[PDB]
Image: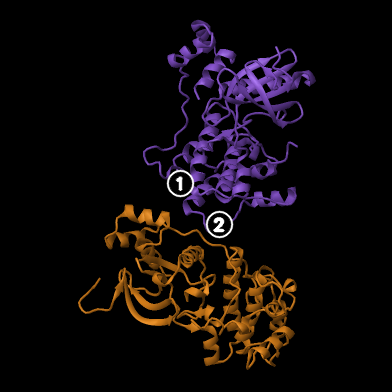
Chain colours: A orange, B purple
Amino acid sequence: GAMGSDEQPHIGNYRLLKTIGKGNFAKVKLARHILTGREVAIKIIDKTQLNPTSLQKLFREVRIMKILNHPNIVKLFEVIETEKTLYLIMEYASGGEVFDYLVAHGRMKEKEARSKFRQIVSAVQYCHQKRIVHRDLKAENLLLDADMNIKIADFGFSNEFTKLDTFCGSPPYAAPELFQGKKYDGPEVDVWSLGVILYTLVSGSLPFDGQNLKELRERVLRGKYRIPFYMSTDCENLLKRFLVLNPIKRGTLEQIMKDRWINAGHEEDELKPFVEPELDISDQKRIDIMVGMGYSQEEIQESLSKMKYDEITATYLLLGRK
Amino acid sequence: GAMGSEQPHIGNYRLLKTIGKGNFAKVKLARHILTGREVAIKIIDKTQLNPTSLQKLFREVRIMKILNHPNIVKLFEVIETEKTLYLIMEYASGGEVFDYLVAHGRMKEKEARSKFRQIVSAVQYCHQKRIVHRDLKAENLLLDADMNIKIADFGFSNEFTDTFCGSPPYAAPELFQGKKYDGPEVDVWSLGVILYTLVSGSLPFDGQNLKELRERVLRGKYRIPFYMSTDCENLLKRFLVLNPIKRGTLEQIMKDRWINAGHEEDELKPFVEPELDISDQKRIDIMVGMGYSQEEIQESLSKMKYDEITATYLLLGR
């Protein structure tokens, strides 16, 4: 309700700073957590505009979001739900989109590229192991935070909840089996997209481009791409593992993590499937601070163990980093 | 005498369809004439048994007489002839829990909860009577007409029920470590596997052959579906513990949050067999109406003979 003399609007314990994404059934605002100081990105979804089927799908998606806990996937911090609106307090990536960065600053050096691709392959692999496939990757799915770390956004989140824009991003990342008419589900598809993502990181360009769809299709179906003169032969070899026309001949991410290029300069640190560490819900330094914010220990233990995504849990998580 | 070439009888029971045929034993649906109640009769050809099998058979009869729990198939009466043995017991019309799962999908946690309290109670009770199964399968959990659990053949061999069919997936990891495979801990692990089926509608560990099964059981990792409450997940982490020493005890597990949700003042606690009421006049008067003497009733009921009076009295209880 109005909070502070002459300040910005608030939802829940969050100060709303500025709209940083508009479009369709959803807005996104930058916000600051009053209790804690952290900045967050808050999804605002108009429930009003949604039918009961959408509504139910949305909630199950929000449930998936809760399960995703990876250093490179944007984390969910809190759900505030009103009568007309749904507020998803997400982790904030100020860096922008990866591909945008690439256009602005040119290609990445293979070392820089490797560091990011490791994170991307780790993140997308973690999602596959949980049987979450996206099958629709666009530039808009890969973000950078203020620390130039990869944050994957909206993975497993359907497009209804992010307007006539649905097909802008997809074709350059779509796998050839879409244009052939063979089945277009399965992690195989995502793998195709990841190879494309690799290419843009090290070349600063799309491996398959086109002035129109006809032209993009032609190239994608044919699967041929410049190996720019600067591209190390190991990088060329990695690409061969991702961009194979026949989907069953593509490498799984689990195998690909063993590749010579992905592991270069990481002798003792071979990339592996990510093992989710048990969330410590007993950090007493953190609990004491919240006691100080006027929350009872009884109530903290409860929201934490229950793992409800309310203001208590959020504060804890945000206290943080994260 | 005969019933007319119409269904045959044995004792006070009329014999309807056969519901299970195995080697050594058959099971027939039957109706108890005096009372109308539906029963299952296990018919065992003594004729074809060597002394050892005979003894195993009688141990299983001893064990049924001890176990009395609303969720363990009860014994009502025994009829023995020099050559045939009939055990008259509760009918479970619902079939096997796992079958019901496969047919109708997983239960909602509220539903899985109330079945699981029944299962936990019953096994803890057997452990309390010092009876440990070490061989939990799907066919050990049946459902009755009212959707209540009825554990069958707990504490038995399977000689009188093809045998290694269902048990590997419920087998405890120590089975594949050449250690000792006894102790209630094994039953506890299996119980963890059963939870998984109730809430998921499938198995936590599976494989196309023994090796594959072993590898997954030994690793002890398993999928947590999106729909599964974190409380349910936490409770599972108390049963599916690779180290037999670190596995939760039933008596402690009964106090779990999940186990008790929607039962705030009615927490799960070890079962306490009440003393059998042998003094229900309402029933006794009905029985005297059937031609039984007042005192032959006490004779039978005190001693607890599993004869025609005892069966009649208990059957009148339901």
Q: Is residue B67 visible?
A: yes
Mark 1 crowd level (few <14, some 14–19, many ≥20, 10 Å Cα): many
Residue A94 rendering spot, x and y as whole percentages: 44, 81
Picture layout, residue A302 above or below residue B150: below
Q: Quadrant of residue A191?
A: bottom right
The residue that disc 2 covers is B225
**Residue under pointer 1:** B258
Q: Residues within 10 Å of mark 2 (few under 14, many from 20)?
A: some
Tell me the element at label 1: helix
Q: In the figure, B49 relative to A140: above or below?
A: above
Amino acid tagged 1: Trp
Is residue B240 in view?
no
The answer for which chain carries disc 2 is B
Asked if both marks, 1 and 2, belong to the same chain, the answer given is yes
Residue drawn at x 64%, y 80% is A174
Q: Residue at x 47, y 51 (%)?
A: B231
Number of marks drawn: 2
Which image quadrant: the N terminus of chain B?
Answer: top right
Distance of label 1 from label 2 (alpha carbons): 17 Å
